[PDB]
Each structure stands twice: as C-alpha cells, then as structure tokens.
Image (tube, coloured by chain):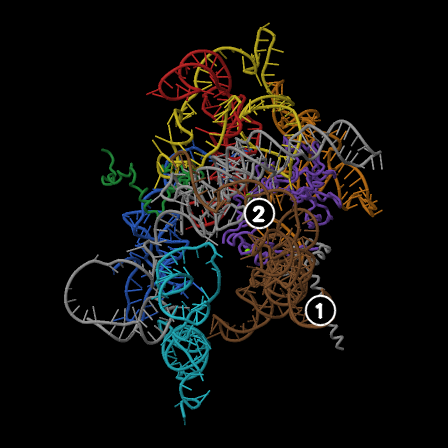
Chain colours: A purple, B green, D cyan, E orange, F brown, G yellow, H red, J blue
Amino acid sequence: GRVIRNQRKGAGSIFTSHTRLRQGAAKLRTLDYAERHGYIRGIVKQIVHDSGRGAPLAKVVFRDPYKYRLREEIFIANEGVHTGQFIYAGKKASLNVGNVLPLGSVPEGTIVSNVEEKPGDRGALARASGNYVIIIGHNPDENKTRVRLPSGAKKVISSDARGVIGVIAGGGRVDKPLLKAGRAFHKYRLKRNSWPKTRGVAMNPVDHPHGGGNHQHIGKASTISRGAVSGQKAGLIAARRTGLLR
Amino acid sequence: GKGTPSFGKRHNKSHTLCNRCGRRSFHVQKKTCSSCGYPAAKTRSYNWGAKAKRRHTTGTGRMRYLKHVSRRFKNGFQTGS
Amino acid sequence: GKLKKIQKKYADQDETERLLRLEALGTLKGIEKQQQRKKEEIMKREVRE
RNA sequence: GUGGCCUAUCGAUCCUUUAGUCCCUCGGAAUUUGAGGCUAGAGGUGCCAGAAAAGUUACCACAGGGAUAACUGGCUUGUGG
RNA sequence: UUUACUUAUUCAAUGAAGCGGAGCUGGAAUUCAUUUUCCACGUUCUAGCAUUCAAGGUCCCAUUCGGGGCUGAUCCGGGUU
RNA sequence: GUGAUUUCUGCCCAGUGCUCUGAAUGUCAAAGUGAAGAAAUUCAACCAAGCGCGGGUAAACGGCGGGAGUACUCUCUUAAGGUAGCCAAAUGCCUCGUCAUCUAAUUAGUGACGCGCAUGAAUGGAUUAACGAGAUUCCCACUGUCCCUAUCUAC
RNA sequence: CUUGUGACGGCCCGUGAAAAUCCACAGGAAGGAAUAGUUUUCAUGCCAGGUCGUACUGAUAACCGCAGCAGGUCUCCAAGG
RNA sequence: GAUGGGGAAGCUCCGUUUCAAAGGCCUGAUUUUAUGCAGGCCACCAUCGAAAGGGAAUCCGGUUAAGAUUCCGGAACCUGG
RNA sequence: UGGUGAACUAUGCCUGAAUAGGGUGAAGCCAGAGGAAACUCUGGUGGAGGCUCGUAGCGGUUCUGACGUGCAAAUCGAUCGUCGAAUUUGGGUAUAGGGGCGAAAGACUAAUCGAACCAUCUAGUAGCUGGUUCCUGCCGAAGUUUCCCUCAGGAUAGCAG
RNA sequence: UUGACCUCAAAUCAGGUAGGAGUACCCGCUGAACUUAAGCAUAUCAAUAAGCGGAGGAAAAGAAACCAACCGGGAUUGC
Ligand SMILES: [Mg+2]
Ligand SMILES: [Mg+2]
Ligand SMILES: [Zn+2]
C-alpha cells in the first residue's frame, strides 16, 4: 500500500498554511509590571481585516514605560470597539468592553475573550469570531477561577490569567451558505491546501483503507481505536457513540 | 501528446557548469554538482562507479607538481646546485 | 488503575457534569441493572419461601 | 500355547519421556546434585518412505506447452435430421 | 495511599525592569495597653503631548565655560519571573 | 460519510468493531516476596494494562424470518423481522412477464400491475425546475442513408 | 480604434507582497554677528563615474522534437472598406 | 543556507534568532601621535534568492558591408567629491 | 546496496502577464398612478451573475474521416465543449522512489509507472526453450520395477559399452 | 583602595597543526540480498558486496591475567 493523504499532511511540503497576507500574530500585551500593579492606556488606531481569519483585528498603540518610543500590539477586535477608543490594560483597569483585566478581578457572570491559559501566554482561548468565555466561579484560596469555554467545557485556570472583556467581532459568519465551490475555493485559498476532499471510499485500496471493491462501501467498521497506528486512523477515531441522536 | 509536442517545451536548464570539474552537472536549485559533489569538501566517488573513478582519478590530468616528486626523491631531495 | 485515570482527567469536574457524562455514556444503566439483579436475587428466595 | 481360525486393522531422523544396566563420561584430582551416553518402549507425521503454511488479480508478468482445454478440419454417429 | 520541601529534571516568557521581606504615609480596624491585623501605597469625559545621566533642594570643587556626590526616586537579600 | 432544493430518513446493539468515571479474581509477564535445597534450581502466594464479566452505540460495519386461522389475527424462530416509498427500473432468472397505448406489423418505447431469483430509506428512499459533445423512444421539417445509381472539379 | 489617467460604483466567510531607498515633522544638543560673520536644501562655477552583456534568428530552415519534421514553444505594436 | 548550539558510528541532520560574553556609529579629543585614551549613541543580529516585482539619471538628427538610447554633432540629467 | 532526476507532468506557494462583439436584464434609484393604511401597478434608469450566443485562447465529442513503413513514436481536416472565471500561462520556488503528488483514472512523477532512471551485487537461479564444430571402423539401447510435494525432474534396478 | 588566586573569554597577538587526494595491501564501524536447502521462515551466501571513519611502506599483533597436565613448554607473525 501507499502512504495515505492524512499521513502525508504532517511533512508540511504543500500543506503549510499560506501566511503571506497576514498582519502578525494576534497576541496580548506582555505582562510586565504596569499590567500587574496598575493599568496602562493605549489607543485603537485602526481595525483591519486579517487574511484567512474570520474576525477583524485591532491595532492598539501603547507607550513603552521604560523608553521614549511607541509599541504597537495586534489585538483581536471585540464587538463594539471603535477607532480612537482608549483601551485599558491592567489589574486596576475598569470593567468595560475591550479592557484587558485579569480574571481574578472580574465578578460572576463576566463574559471575556482572548483568555490566557496560564498567566503570560498572551491569549489562547475564545479567539475565533463570535466566541467567548464565561466566568463561572472564583476560588480565592488556591487562587483559581472556573470558566465555561466555547465548547461547553469547564476549565479551572489561574486567577492571574488575562482576558479581553466582551465577545469577538465578526460573529454569525457560518450562518451564511457558501453556495459555491468557488466560494469554498477562495475561503481555503488563504488558509491552507486541504480542499477539495476526495472520499477515501472512491479510491483504490492502495491509497486508503476505504478504497476498492466492486461497490463503494467501507468494508470494516469506520470507528477506529485510539491505539491504532498511522495509516489506520481514517474514519471516526475513538467514537464513544455514532449516529444522529433525537 | 507526451512525446513530440512535449519535447518542444524544453528550454530551461536544470544543470549548469560546475566550478571544480567543469562538467555541466551543477544543479541550479539544489546548488550541488551531481558528478564531483561541489560544494562538499570531499569529491564524489563510489566503488560501484569504478569506471567513473578511472575517468576522474589521478593521472588523467597534468600532474603539475606530482610529475617531479619521483625525480626529486631519486635525487634525494637535494638542495643547492 | 481506575483511580489513576480519574486523577489524570476528571480532577476538575462537578457533579452535574459527572451525572451528565455517565448518563451519556450509559454506565448508570449498568449500575441500575446490577442493583436490580441483586433485587431479584433476594426476591426469588422470597417467592420460594 | 511367543495374542485373536487365516487373509486388513498402521509410522523414520531430530527432540522429549519411561524402563534396564546402576554400567560409561563430564578431559588438572575427588564427593554429591545436575547433565550427557548405551540397550528397549512411548509421545507422530492418514499427502500414511513422514515440509511448519490463507486468498485475489478484468492492472498483471516470466519460462515453457499443441504432453493440455476454448475454432475449423479428421475418426465415430449416441443424440439430431 | 495522602501530604509537605526545592536544588535534580520538565514547561513558558522577557532587549532577564520593579521578585521577596521589612518600613513609611492614609483608610478600615478593636484596641483592653500599645497596637492585633487587613486593604491600598501619583495615571479613566476627549484619535494632542511625554526622550537630552531631570528640574528643584542640598554639599563639595576652585568658578568659568562648569564638573562631581546625596536626595528627588525608603531600606535589606543579588533567587530574572 | 452522503451529495443542490422539496419531502422524509422506519425496526434491530445478537454478531463484528468502537466506547465507559462499573466490579473485581477468573486469565495473569519481568522485577520483587515466601518456602524447600548445599547451591544451581524448583514450587507457591501476590500480581499492571489488556483479555474475560457488566453497560452504551446503527447519518458504525451491517441485517430486516417462518406456520396456522379468518388484508387481518395468532403462533413459532430469532437481535429484529422490509416501515414510508418505488419497480420487469441501469436492479426481475423465469421473460419476448400480463393488460393498455404507439405501428400494417414492435424481443424496442411509454403508462399501469406486483409473493420483488435478488427494490428500499445519508449502502440514503421518493420527487424534481434548469442544465448535459451522457443513454433511449416517437413526431414534424430535411435530405443519394436507400430504391438505383449517374455526372462534374482538383490532387 | 488602441492606450494612459481621474472621480466614482459593484463584488467578497477572497478586502487583493516585502525590503532596500528617499523626504518631512516633533525635539532643542551645539555653534553662532557688528566691522563682522553665519549659511552651500538659492544661482553659477570644478573633477570623476569602474566591471560584465550588447552581432543575428526567435521559427513551415538559426530553439526542442535522431532532420532544413504540416508538431511544440512567452510577449509588445496593429491601416482602409 | 553558515555560525552559537544540539543529534548522528559517520557521510552529515536540525535550526535561522535560537539556553551566545554575537558588534559598529558619529562627534571629537590629542595635535611625543598615532589613533589609543575623554566621551556619548544603538541592539538588528551572516549570506544567497527576480535580465517580467522594487529601483538615481538621455534625448533628437546623422553614420556602417555588418554596431548603436552605446559611435559622431548638438542638447540634457543624476550620483559621489 | 548506493546514487541521479519536478526542463515533461501532478500539486501548493511567490512574482508577473493575457482574455472581440452581442443576448438576457438582478439589487439600488427616479417619475407617474392607485390605496384609508399596509403596500401595489406602470414607464424609465442602472448594469449583477462560478448566466448565455460567439472570436483569440484552453480543450478534444463524432466522422469510429485522412494518414497508419505518416508531415508526426499521437499528427491533419471538418464537426465540436468552453470562453471573465474552481480561467489560461511565463519565470522563480517546494515536495524524490514503497517515496512524492493526485477534483481519484492506479493517473502523473523527462516517449519509462499496479513502484522511475543509473551503476554494482551479477556471468543472480531455471526440473524449461534453442544451439553444440573432423573422418572411418566395431558393438549397440530405453520409454519398464520401487521410492520421492513424485507426474515436463531425479534416485534405484533393468537394457548397453 | 591595591595586589593575588581560580575559572572563563578576546585579539589580522608570537609560533604551529588538522582538513583534501590516493586507497592494491592494512585497522575498525556499519551491513544486505540474489543464491543453496531441488518449496521456505532458522541456516547458507557472509561476520561478504555496497556505505562510513583512519594509517604506512608495510600495517596490525607482540614480550602472557598464555599454552598445558607432560621428564612440561615460553613474545608476536607467517608456512
Ligand atoms: Mg488543493
Ligand atoms: Mg472498500
Ligand atoms: Zn562538479
């Protein structure tokens, strides 16, 4: 048999992400001294479109506290942020949309976004368009906060992790039908080479586990063990249940 | 049309001249000579290519310094006049 | 061997989620039927007497 | 009288194991375990003078064969007419 | 089996900048004798601006063209976090 | 995996897979423990995961039966017994199925019928405007395809 | 008609390169005049600008298809009815 | 695609700013003077990669058997000093 | 076993380039009319679409035409599909052989692909096919027995010198 | 303040050295399969071919942690 397509994807020859027209990694400002002892005020200069990303970005300018210069950070724009808005980042920042408060200093029921997992990785959770994280509870002794993720999971992270208050702009995108293979082409043309997708049941048996036969059919069960090896994991990996529930 | 019409599309050299051997075996994109191995420090040779070793071995050129070593040895590496 | 896995992946969990996941995985029906099998184990002796 | 009234009713090498001799050897010398030998059986090859063994190929390949099939022709004429 | 500890090992960030402890200065605090503690400990109407070892105060120099120290900007441990 | 829209996607977890935070001596390696021995060693206990036991899962692979009585009911078998739809369909052996229509005449076409060798529901079922160098049947126009051939030009 | 350009409008779950290089602004370091300077982003005046390529075909005969092969091979200009 | 590093028995592989003590920049000061010592500034961090991308500056007339925005005549422009 | 190829072609990236004339007439907007109001109607404007007829271009349906020791190891002629985009294409660049790439044909990877090419191991093995080079003299067969994964082959006995 | 020590650096510091070629023979690493077994998997081919590292006129080995069991021999190498 041959090496199958998902097995070939990990070499990264033609499967790397197309990153020519992207404007930089959208990270939070680094947690130096001002953000953990007070706050700092920056300005939204422009809200721009990011190639291959459903959400817009915001170019926020701060002043460097140690040197006479300007720092320009790329935030993921929250819905409601406008150009010329003052953005406040820090422990003592007031609770408004766009501010970059740590999660220990927000009450119950707060909706945040671009949430750090550990304090300092500059944004990991709820970064796609329309997604958000809800603070479910606090725990001052052994200082942690429980959060509800966009997947519905409940995480318990540190209370020193930061998050931008509000929801990510650009929500409701996937409600519009694409209607066209050309539209899907232009969508994935700026992301990566993973489209179009040939069904493995329509291949030859040298090319896929599902290939072959005088009728297009899978053969064995399509639920694959987690202990399976590379070249075997083609189908529903480690499925607890299948089928459409009612 | 994989034959005669496809042979008309051939006008871009994959290999150019090499600096150590002058062979036209220097791959343009790989930046490596396929015959002598430039720019590696060792020269490309293989024991299965014994006839190629015979083609490029010592004595197939001028031996601009090595022609006189036996004569200087026979005279005993003398100095003076 | 079971107690290692709960510390590994189910440490941060609450009882609403725990009941939801075991109901979605079907182990609760198995626990119910094991206790039911104990109930007819007692009940058949009672009917014999 | 050296099994079944007679003509059928069954099995090599290697390996393991048993019985006998309690005999021979473990090679610097001894004792005791252990191991290896000798003689006679057993564990089995039914493809039965005894390889350890699933398919598919209409994508196919090679060496050959008229020792061998799918046409005609030839012998035959059951069957057919 | 649970549970400390950190220096081995592991992960992450930064142009290794504000770590830890103590002390001021305010507020709450009830003190049962004098302070037990706990929070703070220069910035939020506005798409401006913020840099020249910092101005001021103070002490020297050898005045002049200026120069240096302390404070402004609390101490202590050199564990970057 | 299936393949726009519309309309639906029935029953079955027995088997094969996949999956559990269940319950816990059945299987049970090396290391380690104990006993016997002079030791090599032998024998036991203990014994992780996975198997084994217990659940879930079919838009997972798949599967969707018989005998009586009067379509219906009952009884067996099994995990459950083909539901809604559709059909001599590109899927029907028998088969050139039977009836109607189309023709002078039709193993072709279309519309019906259905004990369907061997239809059937994301193995997707049924329907469907527009589109097609896709496959098939009929009609009008048209003609050397033909009755039945003849003639002319260039090379 | 060809082409350049301007102000617009439509489209996107597509909003459609980077660096060298050059200029300006903020800032006020420093240098500075009166018998004299300060300015060469104003005008004129002086000197130098190295190396390699440079012919021709670009196709029913200059390229590739064994060849003077009806094949293949990127592009600019484009009169009248 | 080197270096610092880390793999690999090794030919070599990874990585391109990384767990590196990674450098040069202008003013000058001195006028035994060479360029150290007075200073002060800055932290990218090799290099290769387009004869269609970016990019300092040239046009007309004439001239040869065969060259020309390149020669000749005239008229310009840019860069460095 | 060790090397060489993405000059053809497959795919992604980077940077460039190319594409007559028509037909239909989408939103938005303007005027008139009607209505009690919701809003409807009529006439314009506008110029949308992986729309359409059709050049250049890209492709290759049929004649199963020509040719078929050809112009040609895939061409020529007519008829065709498509023609503003999932378009066509230059150059640069990346992926290398049990590997790549594949809108999936086991297709393409230099006229080579159900595992490229080059050299070596290698004079690989063959119970199978073909061949096996002067004269004369004398003698002169077998296709049968037994065993064998034996049935196109051997061993053994027989026949012969 | 000054002078040591240790450790770590920088110099177009003073002087040197390594790389590559050849490779018949030599010292190592790595390492097949064709083939034979009348099939084939252990085996064989073979501790070979290919690949990699390193020398010399030779290299390597070499003066016993040896061979022996005898009345004992006496570094290594080769026939
Ligand atoms: Mg793709
Ligand atoms: Mg299949
Ligand atoms: Zn070379």
Q: Which residue is drawn at the image coordinates 72% and 46% (left, top)?
A: A134
Q: Is H52 on the left or on the right of A155, as rendered? A: left
Position of residue H39 relative to residue C33, above or below, is: above
Q: What chain is tagged by disc 2? A: A
Q: Residues within 10 Å of mark 1 (few under 14, many from 20)?
A: few
Depth order, front residue of G65/D8:
G65
The answer to whether residue A58 shows anywhere in this view is yes
Q: Which residue is mark 2?
A: A197
Position of residue E51 relative to residue E24, above or below, is: above
Q: Quadrant of residue J63?
A: bottom left
Q: Which residue is drawn at the image coordinates 73% and 67% (left, top)?
A: C36
Callout 2 amino acid: Lys
* Tag 1 near tag 2, CB within 8 Å: no
Q: Which x, y percent locates residue B68?
A: 26, 38
Q: Which residue is drawn at the image coordinates 75% and 45% (left, top)?
A: A109
Q: What chain is tagged by disc 1? A: C
Q: Which x, y percent locates residue F2?
A: 61, 52
Q: Which mark is residue B70?
A: none
State whether label 2 is within 8 Å of ligand 1.
no
Q: Is G65 on the left or on the right of E68, as rendered? A: left
Q: Is B66 on the left or on the right of A137, as rendered? A: left
Depth order, front residue of E48/B4:
B4
Q: CA distance from mark 1 to mark 2?
A: 51 Å
Position of residue C11 relative to residue G37, above or below, is: below
Q: Which residue is mark 1?
A: C37
State whether label 1 is within 8 Å of ligand 2.
no
Quadrant location of ligand 2?
bottom right
Position of residue C38 relative to residue A198, above or below, is: below
Q: Quadrant of the C terminus of chain A?
A: bottom right
Callout 1 amino acid: Arg
Helix or strand or loop: what does disc 1 sit on?
Answer: helix
